[PDB]
Length: 94
Image (cartoon, rainbow, N blue to C red; front, side, top):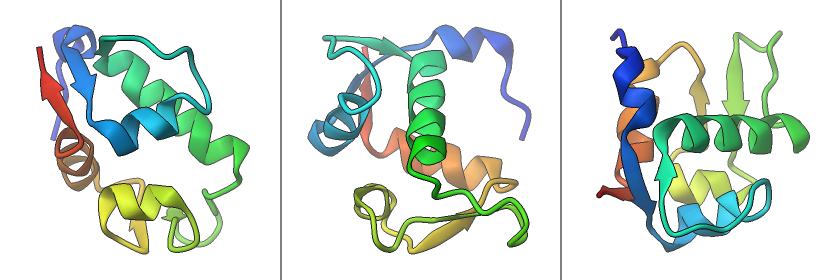
């Protein structure tokens, strides 16, 4: 999957669990862009050290609310379509 640059500007309203996670890294607001959603989720992952780089580029989230958000115990960061789908289940396009 290749995500076009224009999609970074897509306006979305997070559902409550995603909003909860976003508020731990960014300002709460009514609407976000997908650029913001991806950056903030990435920042959440990095700050909490959920990304294991050397364990086959895997994010581990079984002990974290991120796992509740996505409904998986872990995922490969290379699985872009799976990730993007999991994120989109937790928001509404404006």
